[PDB]
Image (cartoon, rainbow, N blue to C red; front, side):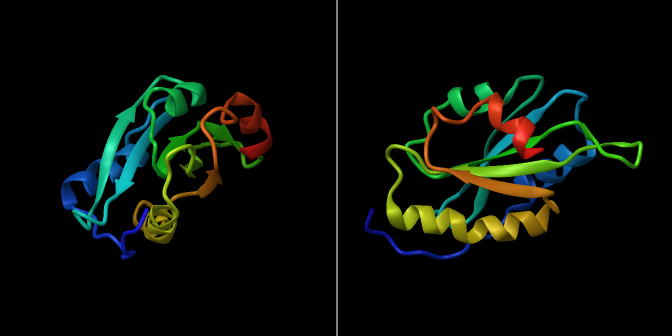
Length: 138
């Protein structure tokens, strides 16, 4: 709530699984929640879960901070192939400090470049994140 803002470096360890997520995904929707910390100054994985749905990804753990969850959904497009459009929704709900928001919102562009993320999204709450948006998000 009173700290400075810098971009984070991605350690190979978490970067590997960050890449493995898109290369080795399920036929269900999976999510990798990751963290940009200024104190480590590195972008590290908070946790990865599979076979669950959007409601769990937001509910499993209280963030009290701008955390971003990369959800990969098996979504087929008109070109006859089932694709894996994964998006990282950085949610800044109850507890999130202003500078930290901009901290995560800052390096969230870099992670989109790292894993070649399909898209990303931001919502300021935990409760209003659920299945309803998926069919209007895709």
